[PDB]
């Protein structure tokens, strides 16, 4: 029952106007109910990132594990935020 | 290779049965997926996501497929049941 809801929710999950940190927390919370393997989860996680994070990621060699990709994207966000100020 | 994998992960997510046949959709899906490293649960869920609504609705009256081939076979039989002369 949880798995069905999770597969729907994760596909709709977006960073959108919000932060990588909140997106990543919600993503891992939902993904714990999924039986997708790590490559599929990485691709879904990337799909939901905001355009500006995806643009920054395109300049970099992207981590090939989900936890490392989350760390990479959080760092990108933190850097852009510190630059804004 | 990594490049084929990147292409595959974008193409599989945009692939849709639309107004076309289950067999054409399924052959295209499996062709793309040969270059992916997603496990069978993730492929099942993506395949379902791309089906036409009229096939998806009829799936609810059937046993839940536990393999990609089983789901494809169900959809082929549903299509044959619904097809106009």
Image (cartoon, coloured by chain):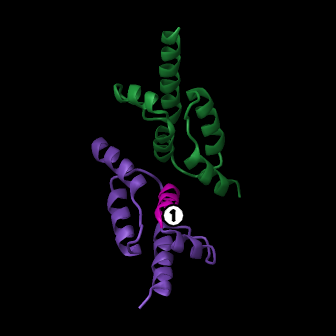
Chain colours: A green, B purple
Residue displayed at 64% across by 37% down: A26
Q: Residue at x 47, y 38 (%)?
A: A46
Q: Residue at x 53, y 69 (%)?
A: B53
Residue B8 magenta: no
Quick one: quadrant of the N terminus of chain B? Answer: top left
Disc 1: host chain: B
Residue at image location 51% in from the left, 44% down from the top: A41
Residue under label 1: B48
Residue range in magenta is B40-51
Image position, residue B15 (x, y; %): 39, 59
Quadrant of the rendered structure where residue B22 is?
bottom left
Left or right of residue B3, residue A1 in this image: right
Quick check: B53 left or right of B10?
Answer: right
Q: Position of residue A33 (x, y in %)?
A: 65, 49
Q: Main secondary structure of the magenta part?
A: helix
**Picture coordinates of residue B9 (x, y %)?**
38, 48
> Looking at the image, which is closer to me, A25 or A81?
A81
Q: Name above or below for residue B44 compared with residue B37.
A: below
Give yes or no for residue B42 being in the magenta stretch. Answer: yes
Image quarter where the C terminus of chain B lies is bottom left
């Amino acid at each position: 029952q949880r798995r069905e809801v999770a597969k729907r929710k994760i596909r709709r999950l977006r960073q959108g106007m919000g932060s990588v940190i909140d997106y990543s927390n919600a993503f891992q919370m939902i993904a714990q109910d999924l039986d997708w393997n790590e490559p599929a989860l990485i691709d879904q996680y990337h799909e939901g990132l905001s355009d500006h994070i995806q643009e920054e990621l395109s300049h970099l060699e992207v981590a090939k594990s989900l936890s490392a990709l989350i760390g990479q994207c959080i760092h990108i966000e933190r850097r852009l935020a510190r630059a804004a100020a």
